[PDB]
Every structure is written in structure tokens, then in C-alpha cells.
Length: 229
Ligand SMILES: O=C1CC(=O)NC(=O)N1
Ligand SMILES: [Cl-]
Ligand SMILES: [Cl-]
Image 1 (cartoon, rainbow, N blue to C red):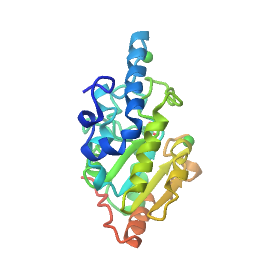
Image 2 (cartoon, rainbow, N blue to C red):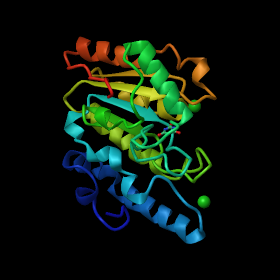
Image 3 (cartoon, helix red, strand yellow):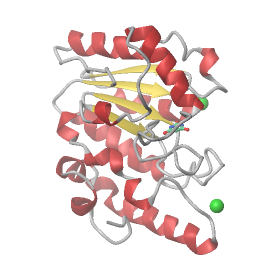
Image 4 (cartoon, helix red, strand yellow):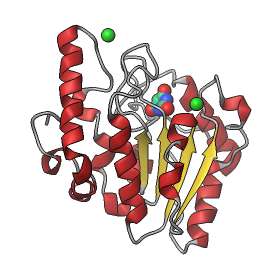
């Protein structure tokens, strides 16, 4: 359903609907923002029904969150899960090829068959962006338009759960969530973003997957099975 018209209880998974209650009005306001963009003749990505897709996997099952900046800017790439693409997309976006190069260097696994990250989402990884929409061809075009309050609320709610959490924060916009992760059940890994523009400043060699698993094991949580087909 549409974010302007329908309540969180309809839009997102039950635990997420309770977690996001402080931003219920703000999510409806974003639906009105997106409506105004279409009225004005501007486009947005991902598709309306995918914008909140990260919050359709169970809140109670999240062990790791990965946070990027904003969705892929090329039509046909963004699917509402950060960095993921549909299984028939080729070539992979360059950021995703960089992620997979680090995945193979860190974990020793072969390169994945395709760019679909839904196994991670189905295994306790929240695939979040700091901002949940973008105008085509214009990275960061929806920065400061109201999504930040929504993703801040999501992180605060996860951090408050009586459960371990590991956050992987890629880039500067994602790292504005670090203050909200201060509680002792939460630990944050931060690096430069995997974009070609920033990856060589510290994404490559950062070993985020193995490190997140070492942190989860030190907190007595089950490691993520990162292996993609
Ligand atoms: O281009 C992209 C895709 C994504 O989902 N997240 C990012 O930060 N960058
Ligand atoms: Cl447009
Ligand atoms: Cl950045």
C-alpha cells in the first residue's frame, strides 16, 4: 500500500510498525512529499511499494544492520534493500561490485552468482539507507527532505531492544547514526562507503563481515551466514 494513505500496521512488519510509531506522521508526510514530486514532474526511486521494504523483514530478528546513503540512482537498480539488485541485473552497480570484492577478500567465498542480497535480509541483516528515496541520476537529491528522522527512529528502536546489535555504517550520512548506538548492547563498525569515489579511502580491506561476526560472538549472539549463492 501507499505511505500517505495507509498506516504502518499495513505498510511494515508488526514489530517495525510499533518501533516506528514515533515517526508515523513523518512517514505519511514523506508520502505527501513523493506525491508532490510526481505532481511536479520529477521521479523517484525505488518504486513506491519498495521504499519501506527493509521494514518488511522482522524487527525482532535483526542482528546486524548495514546502512548506506540513499538508493541507487539508475532506474532498474534500487529495490528498497540497500545495495541489492534484482537477480537478473547485470552488470552489477559499481558499489556492489566493490562490496563483493571485499566479501570475497574477507570471507574467502567465491563471487556471488548475482546481486540479490535478499538472503542477508532473510538471515537477520537490515539493509537500510539513511535516506530512502532518490531522484533518478542524482545521488543525494532527497537528503534533508525528512527521511533522516525515520531512519534515526529505526536505529533508536533497534538499539533499545533487549538484544545484541552490530551496525555497519558505510559513509558519512550513515555515520550520523553513531550517536544513537551508544548503549552497551550495540557496537558500530564505520568505514568509507564502497562507492568508487570513496572506497580506496578505507572500504577495501575493512573486513566488515568477519568483524561483525566476531562482535556478535563476543556478545553471545549467532553470527550471520553471509554466504550468497
Ligand atoms: O548507490 C547506492 C545504493 C544503495 O542502496 N545505497 C547507497 O548508499 N548507494
Ligand atoms: Cl525526474
Ligand atoms: Cl560518504
